Image 1 (cartoon, rainbow, N blue to C red):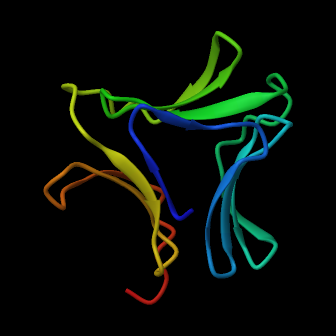
Image 2 (cartoon, rainbow, N blue to C red; image 1 turned 135 degrees about the vertical axis):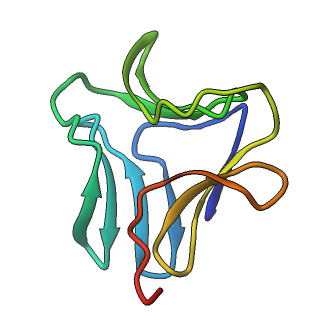
Length: 112
């Protein structure tokens, strides 16, 4: 899929995909955006642990966990609501609320 809804997670090696864009939580615990196999953005958390998952939380925070241990976060926690993470066709990876308001982005947009 191209999106991850709040209250849901990507398991290890799970990803968002849109054409040649791949946003993946890796087994090495690095969260990486690939543009046709070339890394263009990463959380830089390779080697912090293994078997990581990526959780889009109901408080709007995006968090990498290895089991119960927190590894990295977008730090965009706010009030509970419906949020989603999306890999856009312009290569930006964005968290939105329910009203077309971005609360976080990788700023990997191309062409705009």
